[PDB]
Length: 209
Length: 205
Image (cartoon, rainbow over all chains, first blue to last red; front, side):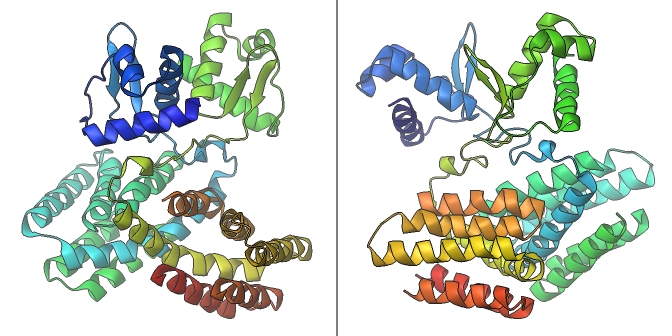
């Protein structure tokens, strides 16, 4: 019943298209719109908060969470003791997924999206050349941006989780050159070349670990 | 500080290799072993419970959760309105991942694991033949079992989430036999191609 009401509550939230950060109607109103008890709606809201869909803000209200249903370590990788094995396993995933991502980006990216990719690529070069350790996080954002522009929704959700785990667990000249080759292939709308450039980058980065 | 002690508590749980369903020592002992206050350990446990790592059972104890740090719908796919597109996108992930899983299973699986796999393959046949709709969930379990036996830890965590999401939104029988045959003959290329053909067929349906 609680899980069922949580489902309908989720369905109500999607139908009304509440943006991120929006305050929900109070629980008296929700319980009436769903024809359930007040205790039932209280538990259903708490179920959706546990799933990071809602944020119960004590003293204010209950809001659409910016987490959009995804926790910090959503696949439970913090419970893996053998982090060397996990790193190798995650690179195996990246080898299987990221070349297709690069191929899809070459195929569908628009000029304004490409402009933003190239700025990030330059920012990475700038930070790398300055010995600025934030380049490691910019590198993650570059791959996440490629996943977004691939147009595969599941890739967009998944690749940040994979690459963030590798980053938390854990040549610079070669990565800069690889990024330039990937951008060049995408700029020339060449999907096979983008695929191969990305494939050779991941294999090189993996070998460095 | 609470989050620092939560990290230290997680480390302690991993060091001591507490299995799923094990009861933690009481919070007095936890705070003593971590050299921290009683109020800090209480919040650290709640932090780990929020992360689906621990289960706080009122009246009983705090336990290693079977969720293993992973919530229901851990990638938030329930918030995606275009379910037809998400389905096609998830099949593209399966096409890219499952053939390598089958390749790895053929390479790695042991005879006792293979017996379990073959039993599930038979259970699926029986359920399909009996018109039992539980075959759809058994099919999900078949792919999760392959991802487990692939020995890739990330695959083991990830493929159940992919296939559970597709599910929530007689050629298969023949394909399962072909895949098992390749695995039983320890033939990774044949297992790869049998799985690839099967996923492309399912996606087309």
